[PDB]
Image (cartoon, rainbow over all chains, first blue to last red; front, side, top):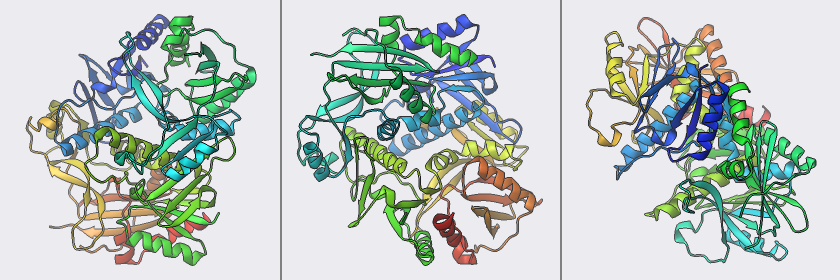
Length: 307
Length: 307
């Protein structure tokens, strides 16, 4: 009942600092676990006899056990950082046992309050489920195809009435002066071919390019909503008010993903329709808070320390 | 409402044949999807406009769409078979988009009856959660340690009263005359060191060796139980009756994993105590059915076609 576990990457700064400070101003104690640093710099131990099976965690000369953890913040769950040119089977077993051990430790925290529960996060990461559920709840989506059939993709390029089509893929953005990195959906233009031997029969996600006057970033924390907008014309986030009908749909989308935290990307078309693009793959909200003074970290701390 | 989807590996024979035939004797139509053959030989397509977003599946010149699927049998969910010496980033994207596309297709079958639902299976695969839950429900487990702290492992070797300790790892068994393969937990004896540079800080699972007069394979299908035993002394499965107190604990274990199908490994000690070892990692039941005429496939077909 005495620490808030904050799960991040070791190269994360602004968002973790704000949440961590908001947590201690509330009276609680945060503990930062860089998940990329397991297993090289983090030790986990658990013993089972049918007694209590609790876990002990050590990281940077600090240590906690699982009954101390009262809430968990899933800022970033990263794959194990493994250094070098390791033999492939040794590597495969290290990575698989590391993931298994971590999953064992997350299960030992099942009674803490999670923002958010890992099973929800893993499911919600899938863009195809997002689109299916968004359209079911009444959100507008861009026409979208997933296929490993080149014929079906060829046919899809003709049904987008007459617009461009892009391929979609999650990527990491790192440069741009600031020393932080972001997860974002890259959009390469689709100009066909049958090459890419190494991707020949591999499925891809294709989506109709939609015209925008605004990009929206909608961050929802436990029923609080925080909205930034960018004017689009090839930026600084600006305030924006969403209609309540859209907010109600977002909550139904969010409760069907089992999530209490979400960052959503929308566009507003010239015609004025809100189009859902995706749950932002990195849950990225730091620019909103600083550029606009939106107290997102406070709402995060509030959920973690008081529900 | 017109096919039972059977998810297997393309090198699976006995178990899929029995279930498939039991299904058609009931009046239903099975459709075999070898998941290892996606994406090279299986085509998946889905289109989203907010209309219906259904999926089309083709495999070996047969095709179905997701509204035809009434039930799904998760015999084997295998990673994508990818052939060759592919460029690592192309490979990484193919594999990640293949998994994403498959997960999209499984979501489109969310209204069919699953044996078992994939979220349960993925969670239940974790041996550490199995042990935690087994001891909570009152099943006896062998003393077990997971750690990447060599000191903690050293200490564990002294607390097993005075028995041998093995390391545990999931592996694939393929030879032994018969042309099928099995998932099983390998047990290498623990004789320490600080080498294995490639596994130096990597967690491992250590377990006290327990004496056995019997190994048990307990297969449960929708509240029906099927038990095989092997006499241990360095075999042919033989009948065995479990006490009802153990059966009640198994059902509580199974309902806490959200599973309607499970293959469990136990040992019976010389002293006569049933010790839980693990949910059999491959759900392996084929030898039981043939060596002992236990109608496991019939119970599987029955669940899939009628609930």
